[PDB]
Amino acid sequence: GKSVVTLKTTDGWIPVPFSKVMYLEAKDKKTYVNAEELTGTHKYSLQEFEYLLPKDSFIRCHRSFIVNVNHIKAIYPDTHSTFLLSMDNGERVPVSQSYASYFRKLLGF
Amino acid sequence: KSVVTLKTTDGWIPVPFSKVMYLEAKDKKTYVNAEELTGTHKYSLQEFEYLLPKDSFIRCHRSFIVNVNHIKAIYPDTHSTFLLSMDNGERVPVSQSYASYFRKLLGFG
Amino acid sequence: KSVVTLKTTDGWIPVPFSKVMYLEAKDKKTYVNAEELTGTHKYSLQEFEYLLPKDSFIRCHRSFIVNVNHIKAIYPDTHSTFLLSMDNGERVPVSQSYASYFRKLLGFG
Amino acid sequence: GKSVVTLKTTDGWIPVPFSKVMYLEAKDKKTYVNAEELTGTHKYSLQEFEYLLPKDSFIRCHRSFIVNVNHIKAIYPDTHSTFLLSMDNGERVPVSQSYASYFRKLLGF
Ligand SMILES: [Mg+2]
Ligand SMILES: [Mg+2]
Ligand SMILES: [Mg+2]
Ligand SMILES: [Mg+2]
Image (cartoon, rainbow over all chains, first blue to last red; front, side):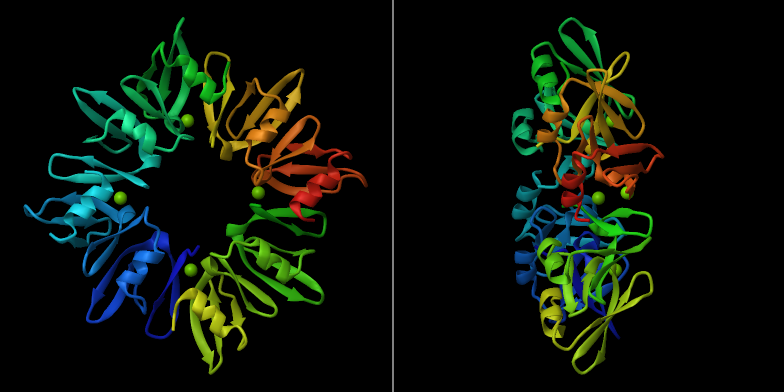
């Protein structure tokens, strides 16, 4: 199918393998692709990325986030209705109340 | 699916299938033994046989599924039986009732 | 297929597709440029488009096919044109006639 | 499908991933599986292995040898009718006159 996402940087564009994408974030009306070594902008929506990203690795976990389960370090029940994801590079990502069942069902816990 | 999510004391930990050494039924619970950690999972060994890659994982005992890629050596320890030396030093049994299936699948005989 | 066999002065060298950076048509001959070496191949660029993985390789010029996994960054160098900075430091063109196809496939635009 | 070959050693059996098999040799009425770190015996014939080994990596190159093209370092035309394969660990493997066309056709040179 496809195996790289092209992030927009200030001067050029950087092809990043899917394997190096940690998460994607909808923020300030754009999609930010957060890769291990850089961050950049993409024109596709999170809805479009859900179609194109491999469903074995990537999961919509919040209206504003797609996470790569291979960069998840730990999953915490931060409150009674949500999760908080500890990423391998120290970042955190929320699983919202509205995605929390889908998230845990798909991940099998 | 790509990872298995192990239950921990404060949370859950996604582990790739490549890092799972073996799974053990114990006390009405499945224990997934990965390189860095062990945790529980809600699926039975029979459910995991369905969902784990058949090229890599094999039920070898009523209480164990082993990842063949973490078997260091296979030794006959009885008339009707094998014993698996794992990479990390541990040892997993192949019971009498699985020894024939086990060797047919791994192709020694 | 898994490897491409490059012709050398004393012989031939199998290179995995992962190690091919780009292929270049020159003088009635295809040059496969791998990380450690360059050699010739009897297949045309058109033949190689058929046989190389579409997720990884793309014809970007009448004289080049590039491996997207060895592109370091993509820069616009003209109205109708891109220039590819490769990992090893080299630079490959995307000609006017391929620039649109190139960006549609890589998903920037 | 399958992803390990079980070699017979003096005391036990050792599962080896296909990726670590360099070549197989029919010799003295047995099959010897030559892996990066050890050698051992298998009950299947070279004919049977041709069926079971991935055709993208493994090739029958001689009535007595199956080679893994991923462990080939260089291919030499040692005479006008044969090739000689330089393996990555320093060993050599012949491509006989009778397999030489099939070998070069499959490898594309
Ligand atoms: Mg992880
Ligand atoms: Mg082993
Ligand atoms: Mg790159
Ligand atoms: Mg090699």
